[PDB]
Image: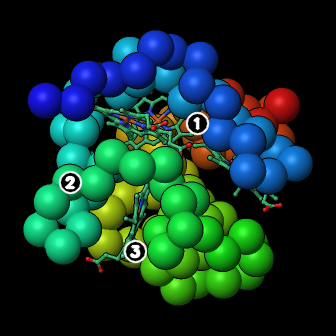
Amino acid sequence: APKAPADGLKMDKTKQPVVMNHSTHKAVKCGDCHHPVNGKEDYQKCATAGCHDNMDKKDKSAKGYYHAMHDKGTKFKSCVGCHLETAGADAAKKKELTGCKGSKCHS
Ligand code: HEM
Ligand code: HEM
Ligand code: HEM
Ligand code: HEM
């Protein structure tokens, strides 16, 4: 079984890099993020070629990297989509977990 990596992982495909900590995400099944592809949970980097490798932030296809991290209504919850549900009606948590600036994702 693949093991979770160390905390402090940088996601740095873009000029707005974000740190991923697995320890804060333990309530989440591995395969909700490392989702099935062709019937098997895929643990490759999300922007691997053929995966979310389209760096146009307007793209909404299954290759759009921005889309996979930010949008609602996706087949697997995105960073922002899950965080919106987590924050609920709490505006402080909305700023912390979903704010586009001054949040725990983006300074
Ligand atoms: C669950 C315990 C779980 C495992 C196992 C796991 C593994 C894992 C690996 C091996 C990597 C490194 C991939 C590489 O080769 O660099 C990795 C990286 C990321 N993970 Fe993960 N992970 C588990 C759980 C979760 C959960 C619950 C999420 C989503 C909340 C998540 C997400 C990520 C992300 C993002 C990365 C970085 C990938 C990238 O930048 O391309 N993981 N994980
Ligand atoms: C890396 C941890 C990673 C993330 C994050 C992630 C996100 C993601 C979302 C949010 C979707 C749904 C998008 C929607 O509009 O419905 C989604 C969908 C697919 N992905 Fe992905 N994904 C990550 C990793 C990987 C990897 C490593 C690949 C390539 C092997 C990949 C591929 C795909 C494909 C294909 C889809 C569509 C799947 C389907 O329709 O069943 N993803 N991902
Ligand atoms: C997507 C790759 C993604 C990112 C990036 C991300 C970031 C993130 C941060 C920065 C925090 C704060 C704690 C920390 O610094 O590690 C945080 C917290 C929570 N997250 Fe998250 N998150 C990503 C994805 C997801 C997904 C897909 C879910 C749900 C399915 C999810 C959940 C949560 C939860 C719960 C927390 C804790 C909330 C807090 O304690 O108030 N995240 N994440
Ligand atoms: C708020 C809705 C919000 C906005 C707007 C936003 C923007 C943004 C940009 C412009 C990028 C770079 C895109 C590019 O290719 O140039 C970027 C990248 C990432 N973001 Fe973001 N972002 C908003 C909010 C959040 C929140 C709250 C999180 C975390 C839950 C988050 C996550 C991510 C991730 C992951 C990336 C990619 C990091 C990288 O690989 O460089 N965003 N965002």
Q: From this view, report whether residue 92 is shown above or below residue 17.
A: above
**Residue ID for mark 3:** 73
Mark 1 or mark 3, earlier in chain: 3
Badge 1 marks a residue whose secondary structure is helix
Q: Mark 2 points at which residue?
A: 41
In the rendered structure, the answer to whether residue 10 lies left or right of residue 40 reads right
The residue that mark 1 highlights is 97
In the displayed structure, would residue 54 be above or below residue 45? below
Looking at the rendered structure, the secondary structure element under dot 2 is: strand
Marks 1 and 3 sit apart, C-alpha to C-alpha, by: 18 Å
Which residue occupies 53% across, 85% down?
61
Quarter containing the C terminus: top right
Q: Quadrant of residue 16?
A: top right
- In front: label 2 or label 1: 2
Residue 78, horizontal then vertical, whole percent: 45, 57
Comparing 87 with 15, the one in front is: 15
